[PDB]
Amino acid sequence: AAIPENGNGLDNIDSKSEFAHRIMLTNLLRLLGAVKSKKPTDTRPAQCILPLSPNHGTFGFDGLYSESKISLETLFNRWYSEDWGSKLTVCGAVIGWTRGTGLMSANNIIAEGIEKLGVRTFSQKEMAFNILGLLTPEIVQLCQE
Amino acid sequence: GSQEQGMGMELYNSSEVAREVWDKADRHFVNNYGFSILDIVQNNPNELTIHFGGAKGRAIRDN
């Protein structure tokens, strides 16, 4: 769950940016914690597929998007340090250049130029295939470990 | 021959030692076999699903 916030720098962290940060980080962690609180057993964990980003402020003027995405990376350490390792299992998918999405719809035209250096840009179906690859039984066991 | 629902639960609620016996048994069952014998006795469900996810669940599966 993300809302589109754009043009918001450090000097314009506005109500939209604060609300977006709530959605992407605060209420996200609250949703995970609520699922944990309502899990009765320790033998059926939930695999949380976290939409991590590789660009933590590299483009800028994205409001608090980078803050939310990098804050999601603390769950990897908190899996060990807290009592919810057996209830939730963290699978952080650092999603790359996805084509057709609003976050990079303005950069579809430069997707080819990006790819020209031997780099891969993804369509929505390809991204879905890759993230569904994180739900295979082997990766599920790996997340549980 | 006699396995009626809720047998021994009066003693379970009244005596600390019966509580200890049932609690030890239920904890062992939950940890090593994935079910609660107290739940089985109190509720008598028709079907019960055991889940083998996680490290404890895989230990239960190996059991």
Image (tube, coloured by chain):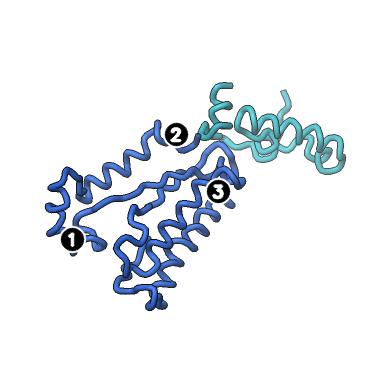
Q: Which label number is shown at residue A78?
A: 3
- Residue A45, placed above or below residue A67: above
Camera-side mark, 1 or 2: 1
Where is residue B32 shown, x and y percent of the image?
A: 63, 27
Where is residue A94 shown, x and y percent of the image?
A: 35, 49
Q: Quadrant of residue A141?
A: top left
* Residue drawn at 53 percent across, 34 percent down: B54
Chain letter of disc 1 in the image:
A
- Residue B13, placed above or below residue A4: above
* Residue drawn at 55 percent across, 36 percent down: A43
Secondary-structure class at tag 1: helix
Give the position of the N terminus of chain A as an image quadrant: bottom left
- Residue A132, placed above or below residue A13: above
User: Type of residue at label 1?
Assistant: Asn
Secondary-structure class at tag 3: helix
Camera-side mark, 2 or 3: 3
Secondary-structure class at tag 2: helix
Decide: few, some or many residues near mark 1? Use Cα within 10 Å; few <14, some 14-19, many ≥20: some
User: Type of residue at label 3?
Assistant: Arg
Inter-mark Cα distance, 2 to 3: 17 Å
